[PDB]
Image: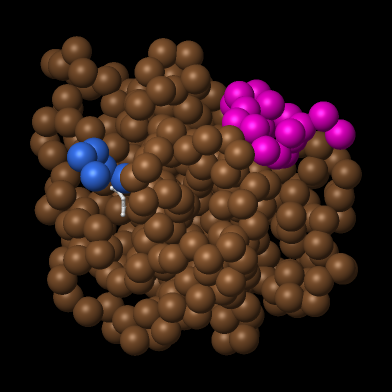
Chain colours: A brown, B blue
Amino acid sequence: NNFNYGAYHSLEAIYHEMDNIAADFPDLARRVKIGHSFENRPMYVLKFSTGKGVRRPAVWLNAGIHSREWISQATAIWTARKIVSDYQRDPAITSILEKMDIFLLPVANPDGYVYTQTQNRLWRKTRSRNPGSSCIGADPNRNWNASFAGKGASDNPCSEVYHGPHANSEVEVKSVVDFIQKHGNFKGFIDLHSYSQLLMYPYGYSVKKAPDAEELDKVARLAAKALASVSGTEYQVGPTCTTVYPASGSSIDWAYDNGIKFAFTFELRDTGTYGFLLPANQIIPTAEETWLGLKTIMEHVRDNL
Amino acid sequence: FNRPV
Ligand SMILES: *[C@@H]1O[C@H](CO)[C@@H](O)[C@H](O)[C@H]1NC(C)=O
Ligand SMILES: N[C@@H](CC(=O)O)C(=O)O
Ligand SMILES: [Zn+2]
């Protein structure tokens, strides 16, 4: 059909392609509205599932929480198409889907993404109003209830890392928290950002060792090796705090502190040559290699089931 | 880098 996966797209085009995927594979993929943004845009996920069990284990794949990181939403929509294309053509994704559901949120910050397309390509935050300030938006990746208002966040609404007035104040973050909590039985939570070529695990808010650190590091290293096998792209691996910087209130620390074992952040390409402004001709190569990383992690979840 | 990622 008429969607170029090697180009960047509007929010409406992305949502339309999600609907197309659900319509073309209605026994595998369903589009679910999980909430809405500050400006009342819908938040949509695709759920990929093969079983009508109750309480089937699930993994959550998150992208585009920071609106300027365009390679994340582009990689996510490509991933949606890859899952449906390869089902019953690749035993790896087929057996993953055999054992677990996958939820994919390609645009976790729709208002910010529209703003980057129409007003300021470098916008990061949400677009919520801050009473008492003319500064707009909170950093949705400092807004989660995991050492909220700790290190690496700001109390200042004008900051790129403003945490918001309280945990879950951003309706885009509350929507995901609420859906995961009600749905239950999550085993993985993977957040796609850019850039730096890093695959990280908890914690961002403290230097303390996650109980599962040895396993998470082992799985991240295998995933990085799989990712590098496609075109040679090298990733560094480690806990967020020392691998990028301290950051409190982040999505993967909230997921892990809530019992979701396989909690990882990818910082996708590149290492700073183009930074957030990654050329469209790198979308498909990035998404192809990232897929082997995501598959490796999900294979590990599968093999624990 | 000079801005958060
Ligand atoms: C955040 O988590 C803490 C855990 O101590 C809990 O007390 C609190 O209810 C949570 N806050 C919100 C706003 O969800
Ligand atoms: N490493 C952080 C980046 C950030 O939010 O500043 C993350 O998990 O996405
Ligand atoms: Zn980011």
The picture places residue A272, in percent across and down from the top left corner, at 34, 45
The residue lying toward the viewer, choosing from A7 and A95, is A7
Q: Is residue A235 magenta?
A: no
The residue lying toward the viewer, choosing from A287 and A152, is A287
Along the horizontal axis of the image, is A82 left or right of A214? right
The picture places residue A267, in percent across and down from the top left corner, at 40, 54
The picture places residue A29, in percent across and down from the top left corner, at 77, 51
Quadrant containing the N terminus of chain A is top right
Q: Residue at point 61% right, 39% down?
A: A281
Q: Residue at point 28% right, 70% down?
A: A239
User: Residue A84 occupies which quadrant of the picture?
Assistant: bottom right
Q: Exactly how many numbered labels are in the figure?
A: 0
Quadrant containing the C terminus of chain A is bottom right
Numbered range of the magenta stretch: A1-18
Q: Is residue A15 magenta?
A: yes
Q: Is residue A265 visible?
A: no
Tell me: residue A104, above or below residue A137: below
Along the horizontal axis of the image, is A13 left or right of A110? right
Q: Is residue A244 visible?
A: yes
The residue lying toward the viewer, choosing from A244 and A110, is A244
The picture places residue A271, in percent across and down from the top left corner, at 36, 51
Along the horizontal axis of the image, is A103 left or right of A129? right
Q: Residue at point 81% right, 62% down?
A: A86
Q: Residue at point 80% right, 44% down?
A: A22
